[PDB]
Image (spheres, coloured by chain):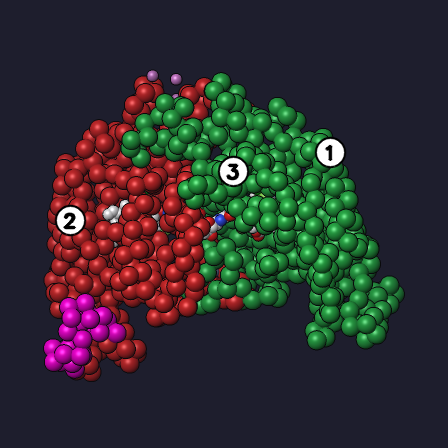
Chain colours: A red, B green
Amino acid sequence: FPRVKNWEVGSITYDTLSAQAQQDGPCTPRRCLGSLVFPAPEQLLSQARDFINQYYSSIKRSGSQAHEQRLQEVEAEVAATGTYQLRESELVFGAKQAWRNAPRCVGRIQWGKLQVFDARDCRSAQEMFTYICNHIKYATNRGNLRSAITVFPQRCPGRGDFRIWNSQLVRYAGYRQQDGSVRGDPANVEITELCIQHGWTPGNGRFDVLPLLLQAPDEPPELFLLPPELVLEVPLEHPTLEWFAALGLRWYALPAVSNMLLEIGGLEFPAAPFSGWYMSTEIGTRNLCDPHRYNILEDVAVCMDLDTRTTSSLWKDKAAVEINVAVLHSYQLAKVTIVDHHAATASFMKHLENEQKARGGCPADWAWIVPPISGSLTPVFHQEMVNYFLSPAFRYQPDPW
Amino acid sequence: KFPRVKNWEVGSITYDTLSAQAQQDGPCTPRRCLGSLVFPPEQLLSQARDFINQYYSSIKRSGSQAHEQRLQEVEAEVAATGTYQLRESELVFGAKQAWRNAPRCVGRIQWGKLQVFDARDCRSAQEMFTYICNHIKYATNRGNLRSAITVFPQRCPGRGDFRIWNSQLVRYAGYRQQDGSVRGDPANVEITELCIQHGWTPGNGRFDVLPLLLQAPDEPPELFLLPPELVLEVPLEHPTLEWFAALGLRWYALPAVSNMLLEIGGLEFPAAPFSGWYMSTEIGTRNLCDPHRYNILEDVAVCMDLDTRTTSSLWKDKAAVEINVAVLHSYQLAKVTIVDHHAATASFMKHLENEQKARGGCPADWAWIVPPISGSLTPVFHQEMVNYFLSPAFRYQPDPW
Ligand code: HEM
Ligand code: HEM
Ligand SMILES: Cc1cc(N)nc(-c2cc(CN3CC(F)(F)C3)cc(F)c2F)c1
Ligand SMILES: Cc1cc(N)nc(-c2cc(CN3CC(F)(F)C3)cc(F)c2F)c1
Ligand SMILES: C[C@H](O)[C@H](O)[C@H]1CNc2nc(N)[nH]c(=O)c2N1
Ligand SMILES: C[C@H](O)[C@H](O)[C@H]1CNc2nc(N)[nH]c(=O)c2N1
Ligand SMILES: [Cl-]
Ligand SMILES: [Cl-]
Ligand SMILES: [Gd+3]
Ligand SMILES: [Gd+3]
Ligand SMILES: [Gd+3]
Ligand SMILES: [Zn+2]
């Protein structure tokens, strides 16, 4: 079992949980590919059997009558139908486990506190839309954000998938420009074009909230505008740089990923949007300062009267820190939940400790857990980590177009 | 079987075909990635054959008279002696290759410019000291630093190694207390205790340059005072924070790693100190702000009158940036070569581009290439990378005790 050191404290642990890693990653003894962003009834049964074992362990009923009976029921259902259905309590447990198992999530100290909306009876894209609106409403909670997932019907033989075409429930449009530039968010050019192609009348601002493209089984995607009073946004200002407000920057309250596949015990839920709350570096560092995103770093630095003619003035570092200060201040001012990267990584360290006691390890992707500014100022930088895949899991999947 | 590698800032794609040549298996498997872990008779002929072939291809002389002749001589030497001697030009070529192959080095744009001092006729620790003193004076060059390596005799069976017990040629002492805590550098408490144990009168300061412990084969180490005029140091001041000087901080000019093992063509050099120049985050972020190093961050924030009562003021990030400014300002004022993390990573992207054309890829350790502050503000953050072991190489080796 891999030995793991924390270099700040000197403590050492062994990740025994990694030995149970079912599915395989991209690395080999010849080469490590850890930095890459994107690396049959019998096999359904063995996946299902392992999940049921997980579930009955969690409720202190391993080896019990109810445990063996459920294993038998699942085998019989797979034999008779090619698939099986989760019980409601199994779905809740499995959704929480998938979050808990997500190696790239620094917010997992919260994994036990997750509101699970069971939408597996959803019949249409129109009912899908209503479920999504109520997710957004519940999760936003007027700024006091609450973690939630809504689970739409599973993939099954004989029917297409439910899919949310949007990568998040709330996203800003990206309009390819006349001269080849992008107005708004360059990350969203593709989905923006698809929305227009599907009847949306575009805007022309930098922060136009996109409509939803929702796909019911064997249906074209259908366009739905979000009710604007459901989409809580935060205008960005800085506590001491009064000109910052004149940038006209905004971001939205709710980070709700909507393009990932939820896998539980072999069953696949291609539509299962989940939401928490932001860590401020996601907005202030990546979304606003990535060169291929809003790319505001140099404009802020010039307004700050920094010397942008030389790298050794650290103008980039200074401007990025104040942009992150603006995000934290603005969300706090607006009474919208947000966590800074110091508080988040501190809580993740407690999560690793909890998980070492509970499970003998914790799958974690160092390059995603360490924040994109001030890396070695946070405790996770000095913590060696073991990255591996456990199920239940959130998985990437191809775009439906 | 050729990993696809994407740069996410630009969208460009390359394939690392060089990875298909990796010799020493790394620590990762398809079941788990260990990429964040700091530390994971005549097969000598196959390693020598391969290295000789490397040398002659690099001079456009594969399959020619001198190539075959050199192949026979190493064969004859190993048959008659069980080992072989590197030609002078081969030692130079191999040192530069080991540097070029170092996956954790962001400074490899310089790999072609390296001064190699051949100390393979060395004997006794007194000779090492004069060799080390020659290196330090050459490398330091009154602040206009020049990359250099000194290669002491290779390991041979039945006889002890040449070893430098210090991890660097210049290191500050770390002294315990009437209460456990350390005055000076906590990274060097052990070698301080070893140096004192061998007769060195310790100082009482936070920045006392340690003596050298130099080990001739099968002899105990010998203490050597470094000539103080040969140890160039930089008092740290800040361009605008007038009180920063009064903190009494210093760092040394020359980063000279002296505990790693150089391996060329199957031959091993446990004493081969190499030096370049600092990247400013090494000093300003890790050495001065790591909690287990000088841990100065909060003292600087107090002096800056920052709100240390909440993490979301980003007082840590602000104090860190100003410490890095102070490092850069002070080295530039002292006319000592230094490179900031923005300049260094941009040069590394150019190195990756050069290596793509020259060799079809480049072994790179993402977690070590991305700087410890402002990670996603540097281009390497957005570059996918492949990590693997090529030879010649710098390897880690156990403490010689
Ligand atoms: C409660 C507050 C939460 C915080 C502060 C948080 C934080 C984060 C952050 C910073 C990332 C990296 C995202 C990026 O760089 O793009 C992430 C990834 C992720 N989070 Fe969490 N998260 C939270 C809640 C949740 C919840 C409720 C779930 C699921 C039930 C979840 C599942 C995931 C997954 C699957 C990823 C990986 C996404 C990917 O790699 O594409 N997170 N989280
Ligand atoms: C010339 C300017 C140079 C710069 C700016 C530079 C920069 C760096 C940096 C920042 C690191 C990370 C080390 C740490 O985090 O403590 C590193 C590692 C390393 N450097 Fe360079 N370096 C330079 C020259 C050299 C030379 C001349 C050699 C060898 C001949 C070399 C070989 C290495 C090796 C082997 C490592 C890996 C250390 C390890 O794996 O622990 N570097 N370099
Ligand atoms: C629940 C939750 C909370 C939170 N704080 N963040 C996220 C979150 C996750 C991602 C993953 N994306 C796919 C990619 F790899 F492209 C990047 C992207 C974002 F923008 C996010 F906000 C999700
Ligand atoms: C030639 C050169 C230039 C430069 N800029 N840095 C280094 C350098 C390398 C290391 C590696 N060490 C192993 C560990 F992980 F323990 C840390 C440590 C340092 F302190 C350094 F300064 C070397
Ligand atoms: C190429 C590299 O893996 C990529 O830029 C990663 C690095 N770490 C990350 N970490 C987080 N949290 N989010 C990201 O999108 C990324 N991107
Ligand atoms: C645990 C983690 O691997 C460790 O802290 C690493 C991370 N990246 C690093 N990167 C560099 N350049 N130097 C280091 O010492 C480290 N330390
Ligand atoms: Cl986002
Ligand atoms: Cl150092
Ligand atoms: Gd003002
Ligand atoms: Gd303007
Ligand atoms: Gd005062
Ligand atoms: Zn790996």
Residue B153 in picture, x, y percent from top left: 76, 58
Q: Which residue shows up at 43% across the image and 44% down it?
A: B180
Mark 2 surroundings: few (<14), some (14-19) or many (≥20) residues within 10 A: many
- Which quadrant of the figure has residue B399? bottom right
B185 versus A110 height, above or below:
above
Numbered tag placed on residue A135 in the rendering: 2
Left or right: where A210 falls relative to A305: left
Q: Which residue shows up at 78% across the image and 72% down it?
A: B82
Left or right: where B209 falls relative to B342: right
Q: Which residue is mark 3?
A: B184
Q: Which residue shows up at 70% across the image and 50% down it?
A: B222
- Which quadrant of the figure has residue A398? bottom left
Residue A152 highlighted magenta (yes or no): no
Which span of residues is magenta-colored?
Answer: A50-73
Task: Give yes or no for contact between labels 3 and 2 (Cβ–Cβ under 8 Å).
Answer: no
Numbered tag placed on residue B141 in the rendering: 1
B65 versus B118 height, above or below:
below
